[PDB]
Image (tube, rainbow, N blue to C red; front, top):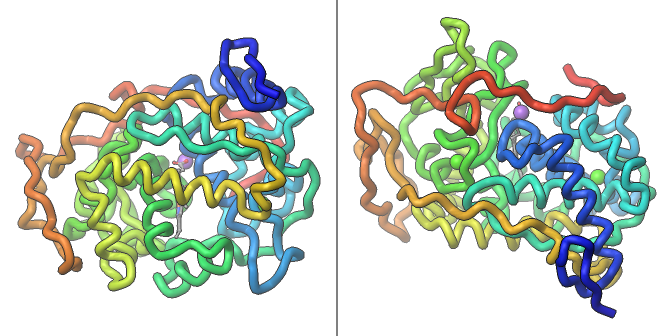
Length: 366
Ligand code: HEM
Ligand SMILES: [Ca+2]
Ligand SMILES: [Ca+2]
Ligand code: NA
């Protein structure tokens, strides 16, 4: 039967109401209403938790979106491909005992949905509940890495859950709110687009610009040249320059994926809806949805998309594009004014001094 939660929310199932206080605690204790570092980490964790599953190897290889990262924090978070995932894992573990009726698998996915809701332009994703509260650790080798080629990436996603090339590119819209701490050992929080606190299509445009240098070292595995490498970290600042992943570059230019990649440029609603659909599929890997219950109503309404059009960042323009898609013309867009690169802020408030919640815990890094 239907019910009304303590916050006034109408749900199709009263068990959904347990998630209301969980969302409140996730915000008050970790996410702080922001599309910031901790939100980004948790969204990355939804993927590392979910994708560790394989049709061809069978169920013993991993249970998908099963909370295995939280329940066995000494195993998967320390595999090489998950270096750095410990921060999100250690931030979520305490919620398992604070909200003991909610499984680790549900916790990971619900935290991701709440985190996304803090990001202007992000979709309000589906949330199904009821993932069982026990599993085993996945094997190593199931998480794509940034040095991987497109054939490998596409095969891994197909084997994980039958994702199509379009769905893979759609999921990578998440790199619109993403930075790197481990790719370059000399850099912290190197952003993948110029708006890492905004769920927009800048990532799609900016990967298509010609690379001109590196924000740090020039020879890191999985990294390629960036179109906007300038930061202020050489003078002690925290506004790290923009980083480009080899995998994002490869997706942007491969015949299977390049038109899907370009098709999101300046198509905010199409991008966000496409991400939402593929992400809902990711979130239930390892489960038959018939065995889950719809608790989508308890995902917070996301911050609205920003008013700002999609534009070329200062000092760039259409002459800098490297295009690969014949099927669709790249749209005419304005160029942000300015003679030098604009520093990409380290914080959603535009400053450099913001700090993030980090709980101690059992997962480790490097
Ligand atoms: C081919 C598939 C993918 C590859 C190779 C990849 C690679 C990476 C790498 C190397 C980083 C930086 C980690 C670090 O050094 O700190 C990163 C960050 C991130 N990834 Fe991906 N990723 C992929 C797919 C996805 C998907 C499917 C999602 C979610 C739907 C996702 C969400 C994120 C987020 C939110 C971050 C930022 C984390 C932070 O700023 O703390 N990624 N990814
Ligand atoms: Ca898992
Ligand atoms: Ca962005
Ligand atoms: Na990070």
